[PDB]
Amino acid sequence: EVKYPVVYEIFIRSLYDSDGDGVGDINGVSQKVDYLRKLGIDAVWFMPFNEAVSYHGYDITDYYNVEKDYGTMEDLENMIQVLHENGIKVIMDLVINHTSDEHPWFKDAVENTTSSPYWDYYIMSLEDHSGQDHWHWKINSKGQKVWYFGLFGYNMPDLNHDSQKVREEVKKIVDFWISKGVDGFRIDAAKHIYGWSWDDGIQESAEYFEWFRDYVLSKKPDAILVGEVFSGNTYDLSLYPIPVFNFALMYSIRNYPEGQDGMIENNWVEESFLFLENHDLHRFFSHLQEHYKKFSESDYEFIKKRAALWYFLIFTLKGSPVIYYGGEIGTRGFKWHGPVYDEPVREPMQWYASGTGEGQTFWTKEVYKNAGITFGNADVDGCIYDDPYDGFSVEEQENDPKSLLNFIRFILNFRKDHDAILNGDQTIFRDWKNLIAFYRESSNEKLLVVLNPDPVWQNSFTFEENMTMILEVDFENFIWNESNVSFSAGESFTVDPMKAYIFKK
Amino acid sequence: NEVKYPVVYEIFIRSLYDSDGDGVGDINGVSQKVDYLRKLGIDAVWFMPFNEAVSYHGYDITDYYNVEKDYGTMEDLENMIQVLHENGIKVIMDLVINHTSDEHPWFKDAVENTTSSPYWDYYIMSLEDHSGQDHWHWKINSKGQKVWYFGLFGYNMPDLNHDSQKVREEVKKIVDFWISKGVDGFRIDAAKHIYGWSWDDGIQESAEYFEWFRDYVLSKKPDAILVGEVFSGNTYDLSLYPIPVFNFALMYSIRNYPEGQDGMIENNWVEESFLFLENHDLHRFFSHLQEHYKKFSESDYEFIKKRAALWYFLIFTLKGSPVIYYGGEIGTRGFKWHGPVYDEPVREPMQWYASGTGEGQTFWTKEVYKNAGITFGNADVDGCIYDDPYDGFSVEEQENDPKSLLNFIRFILNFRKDHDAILNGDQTIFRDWKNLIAFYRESSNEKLLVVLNPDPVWQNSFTFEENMTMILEVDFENFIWNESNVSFSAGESFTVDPMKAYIFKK
Ligand SMILES: [Ca+2]
Ligand SMILES: [Ca+2]
Ligand SMILES: [K+]
Ligand SMILES: [K+]
Ligand code: NA
Ligand code: NA
Ligand code: NA
Ligand code: NA
Ligand code: NA
Ligand code: NA
Ligand code: NA
Ligand code: NA
């Protein structure tokens, strides 16, 4: 009964360690269900929890088992039950573009070549493919050289989705996890299902998800589906027959954090999931710092205010908003380019003022130590982009009325009470740099949402019908209230710089 | 004998060539490397700021009328301009007039003497309280008055007040002065920000400002080169300016779609804009491509080289002045950092030698990296995070290697010199597909058809609208090129394979 649930993206390894090895785990997730519920989220998307070679989980070796680092199948079933009991759905990261090169299917294809049932699961050859783009090779025990295609590299051989066996195997994976209680799927690398290069075959990849959608919805009509199509082009995003993450809006906001004429209409993708950061990007807070060249601590409050304003927008626009774990406390982080790469935007969630306490994950500390990184005291406290006592923690923000955490909790709690946002259509009313205004309307409620992201210039509009102000936000003073004020059709309303309002019919 | 679209080489003096041994690239060093520049096929050099300034990059100026001492003397500069001129190379000065250093004597006087200072009107200053207002800063003078001032880029970069006619007169005077030194044109820093109370405020007002600036400069020197740095990927914003600007839209589009995209040329077109693939504020293009493909291994260098080469080919044949950032021609690597260093790693010592060391090699970064505790890439030892000894990335290793990026670029630039249609011609789009970029260049003296297929997989084809002769073929996948002529007739069909380019002549 909620068309546009709020999604929380969790990296299990960095959330909560329930047994002391420093690694976030599945029982750890269950132990933080109260925090999730109070945050106001409707669903969790987990980064991959299948058995996999690498820490991030995107190179899978068993689709039907749980990564041992995270726990057991029993743990997973229990956690799904706990989240459900708390009104929270579970979205599974489905990684079917490729497997690990350590997947038993692939190992068998390498060993037994054309005699292997899995030879046709992949894109393989015994003919020399040296020098060809994205082709790799292994030598099996018989000394034979086996060539295979792998867009993402030698350790991620591509699956052959022209094989009906592979399609049946995808159906079995879907069936299996639906039987465990999973509520939907986030489909990894949805851009690349087909294509002989990075930007080849988006039409064929989109077409693939017609059969996939039909199958999943046949088994579970209310299933959540979202594809990761890593493109900022609205045409590419709109091609897909399933919802996708709206990278266009995300990039637009990052490029124009003080607004831009036409921002909403120009980056609109119907039914898309709205977000500001994820496990593949610089953290949004850090991006804003870089944008403003404001890297010092006296600029934190300045940055917080701009961040909050764009969260407000994706929480009120039509579509499902996605919060990346820790985004709600302003978690910082930049991708690196060696000797570590995406670890620093996937760091331990900061529960504690001091950076340490019960359940605190710290798996990164050994990673950073072995890599020789001491910047940010990373090799001792585990985080390049967080320090003890710096205000970035759940503990420090929890009872602070001006924290980003409590703003987000406030808006998400507000959101639950308004069917026009949860289920409604949308009609853009204004789409200017300093005046974003849109109606949300379901059969039960009609709202007008307005926001001025410009730090300098006010704007105004005339009411089209009688409405009541039910929310006011002042991002510059960082205060908000729900005092009701009536307005009449024909009345002019001024929207000051960095304010937002919601009016109700 | 005019060239409307000269090839520009962007030089960071500190990182090019050290002529006196302190490890700091200097102006005499530039003169000593004039043969390399001429032979590369460069028509003009744009120098990062060489005025007296606080920081290593030069963008916080304390004297518009003197040369930074790290780089040399005014006499050095005059001789260097002479040397480049004698070699057919023009000189473009980085003109930084949005702001000065807070250590500029004008600003110091304004703070100290307030409304009695001749320079009070030069800045955006006030004795009224501005606490809490964004981009407002203050200093307290010797009389204990708190002086407030606007500084978009920060407290140490107070904005000049361009609504003041005194500041307009000062700008005229700076321009006149450097013109009298033989400077051939100006790259205008932060042209997006001349006006505006915030980062994205006042672009129209800033564009309007350059009408009077252009009119004044051209009145003094009709053939002056002008290009504004407007840091925006929006073609409408870029096209608003009455002077040429760097085409950030095309650069971002190529970086986002390095295997082509429908409408690439037309959707990112900015008339008279300067074309480029990297600069001193961006990740190096070679490194960008590595990240894009997740190909950071040395076994992938060849693969990356080929892609880099085809986009250089494009910006060397499209209408506009192409700009090469120093070391781009050997595929120099580099990522911006976010602490303890920032843009230093994309502004590292030019790699002249296979070994990393040799006469004139700059190494000013070695101390920077040592003091910041950076040992990655052995940087505290050889001064480069993003270069190693004997790794193939140097002028020495590439200069006589037939398949090097340097030899390809040098080849195309010297080819370019012989074709008036590129140097001076108009442009007419013929095809604008992901796997078929094709456009005419035509001057009164020559007509060309340029064709490129950046798609690594899918061929395409077109039909000739008139008889033309193929005068260049480039195979990027095999990394070979040739100028053996082949005639073609109107109505004849031509197939453009993946990763190939052609130039046909009427
Ligand atoms: Ca902290
Ligand atoms: Ca080298
Ligand atoms: K992934
Ligand atoms: K600059
Ligand atoms: Na654990
Ligand atoms: Na694809
Ligand atoms: Na694929
Ligand atoms: Na830290
Ligand atoms: Na020197
Ligand atoms: Na501006
Ligand atoms: Na300014
Ligand atoms: Na090095």
Image (cartoon, coloured by chain):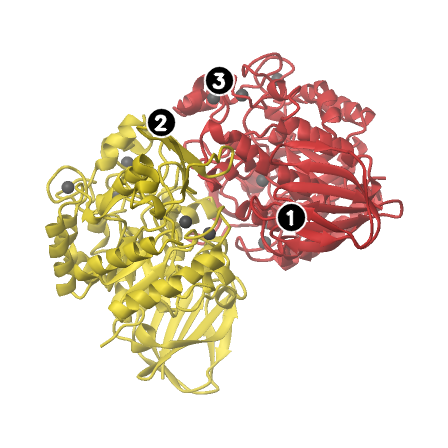
Chain colours: A red, B yellow
Coordinates of residue B148 in the picture (x, y in percent): 41, 36
**Number of the label disc, if any, that sits on residue B440:** none
- Please name which of the two marks, 3 or 2, marks the residue nearer to the observer: 2
Q: Are marks 3 and 1 in contact (CB under 8 Å)?
A: no
Same subunit, tags 3 and 1: yes
Q: Return the chain for callout 3.
A: A
Query: What amino acid is at disc 2?
Result: Gly
Find disc 3 in the rendering and name its residue. A381
Classify mark 3: residues with Cα within 10 Å, few (<14), some (14-19) or many (20+). Answer: many
Dividing the picture into quarters, in which one does residue A76 lie?
top right
Q: Nearer the viewer, residue A112 or A56?
A: A56
Query: What amino acid is at disc 1?
Result: Asn
Q: Return the chain for callout 2.
A: B
Classify mark 2: residues with Cα within 10 Å, few (<14), some (14-19) or many (20+). Answer: few
**Number of the label disc, if any, that sits on residue B144:** 2
Locate ligand 5 by image quadrant: top right
Same subunit, tags 2 and 1: no
Query: What amino acid is at disc 3?
Result: Asp
Give the structural element (helix, strand or loop) at label 1.
Answer: loop
Coordinates of residue B48 in the picture (x, y in percent): 28, 50
Find disc 1 in the rendering and name its residue. A246
Coordinates of residue B411 in the picture (x, y in percent): 26, 65
